[PDB]
Image 1 (cartoon, rainbow, N blue to C red):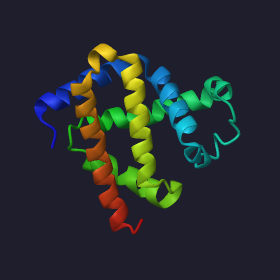
Image 2: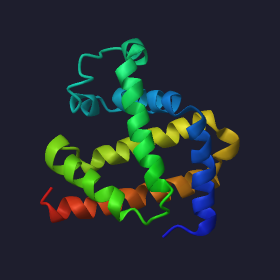
Image 3: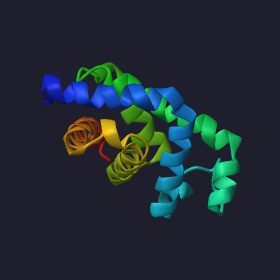
Image 4: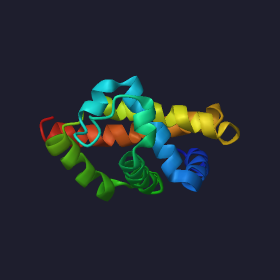
Length: 151
């Protein structure tokens, strides 16, 4: 459970991500794909991308980035009450996309990395801890649905 003050830190920084959702999505996905190239392999739509410059140039990548960040934004603003948001995301990612829970840890590290680059003054260690906690809650709840489904 996050405190209200921890939720506030999380949503203050997220309100800023929301000023340039596409730009954040690019940075986060490039970071993910470069740090963890196995993750790129899950996306038939992106597996032709072989350089950072190709990734930066992809309009569809930027579009998909907005998709993921939008779904995340919606979850975070539930401040833990995200059952309705997670159940379809858990089903498709476990059963259709085949995304290990570990990959959700990887994208969480990428989000934190980028948030830290772009919003130092609104993402000190306190807000980093709160964001960590929120992302772990999301993972924990997803993992429980994976285990139900036998993934």
